[PDB]
Image (cartoon, rainbow over all chains, first blue to last red; front, side, top):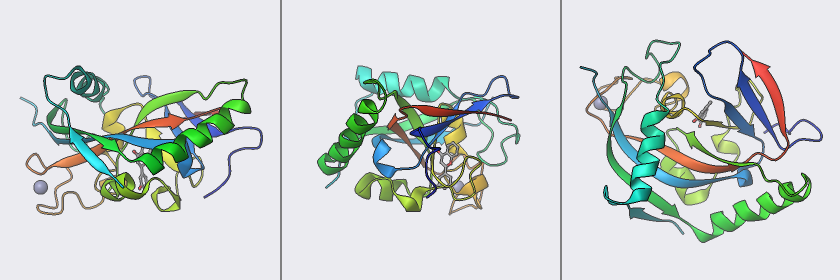
Length: 47
Length: 161
Ligand SMILES: O=c1cc(-c2cccc(O)c2)oc2ccccc12
Ligand SMILES: [Zn+2]
């Protein structure tokens, strides 16, 4: 993996085009995330 | 080290995780190519992931970040989707779950939109779709996402399209 920008712990990808998109985030250390829920699902065919 | 606990549909915790999953669906700019065409999910199961070693590894790092950032970890709950989720829940996030060609460099990526992580469940760009029908929009096959606790600390703000 790469490193964080110096003086920072993650990168925030702030959408500047798609007005409905929420943010995406990047960490450069596996220890900065815990996998808390496993969700099993099907996408549903719209009516 | 890992155990999975099923939540009842009657449990408020089931309900609030289902609501964050359902309410953060959006349309995507690929028209469904990567992740399929849908407005909502049929949630079949929600399991809580319990592993002591992986939890302590997380909280150790969270305190470090917090002390480098005026006691603020800047913690969020975010989605992650991949073909490696059954490995992540057992051994935790590392180098192998990075997105080497990701736009912010080779690190591990998370989304506020559940439907964004859904695009990565069968691989980058949705891969070749479900293993059984080879369909990126399969409505029959069971899919899995992670809903994760993530420490951001002082986040470098990248504006982007
Ligand atoms: O959930 C995600 C998984 C992945 C992903 C990408 C490559 C390899 C991988 O194992 C997961 O990428 C994302 C990018 C933006 C937002 C969320 C994700
Ligand atoms: Zn299928």
